[PDB]
Length: 204
Length: 178
DNA sequence: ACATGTTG
DNA sequence: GACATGT
Image (cartoon, rainbow over all chains, first blue to last red; front, side):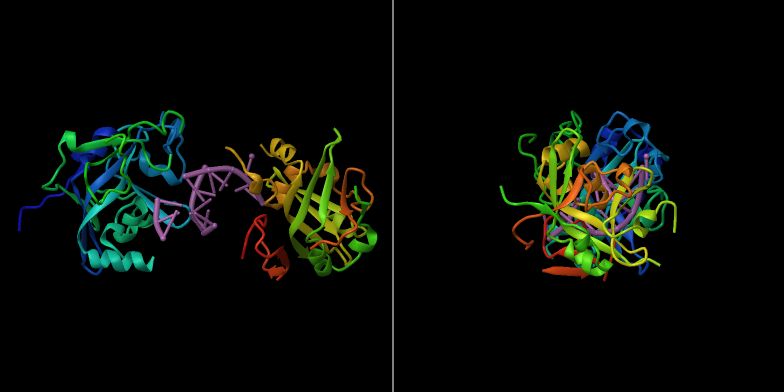
């Protein structure tokens, strides 16, 4: 096989916009306790900018027990429970209380395991087409909160051979909401990808 | 208009379970100092069967006595003394019937009709019921009553409390559905 | 007790 | 709807 090295601190240590963009095309890898490796190529992300960002958990420099990850070293995972039963997987970027949410993966490996995991918690485009869908598919839960994506043995990021060029990256309004921050183009996805959670035609 | 009287001692002077069930479909009325009348149909209650505290004296008074207490230093719960040593019924939810706009300004996001009275503390806020109501008599008070029309109220579910919680089956106004 | 925040 | 979290 090819020489494989994980993306580390150097990759994660950039501001939220460039990081959210840089994630696109990179391959998120999960290794289950049974040894099964799950891979999904990132096709959709969102930037949360920090204190000024009315939509961010870190609005006004607010640090709470839950959102510790957003204020930890870049690369630190911030995984929280939303609507009681779903997870959102974020990665702390450079910048006070700034992070990147992963929203959608093209599944590459272990699709049958992703299917088993999600059906318990059917189509391939249904597996990772959403921030909480992808968490289920890759057995990611709160136990991953505050772990380091640069160093962890169970989850890591690999440089992916297929990165979108600037013109192929769509910038669009974020999903799930405010004010001027509900409309800001802080969601980024690969143009024409069928794995993306929500298409935005006006932005395209 | 119809000949309206109010429910009195005879209605309230029953055990906590019969009364908690009997409250469902009755209309609670609150008249504000400005003359505005607020109305809400009781759709969810809880019976408390008793075993004496400086705060629970209300539930140890004659049936129909209000027991209103502060919880989490902010909210209110409205309870009505029934027959039985220390027994009472909590009001948990109302269907808002009139004065909804007042209910909204008293409660004030954008909140809809289903958010006005869908909770024991929501309903007290909505009907301006506070501590100054504690130990008042529901059968005789001038600011708050349980009205009685020429028609009886209109299906009751007995569930665990939040089988001593009772609510109108499938009502969109019940706080928590089992 | 309340207010509020993706999936299907 | 969840139900985890933040006066």
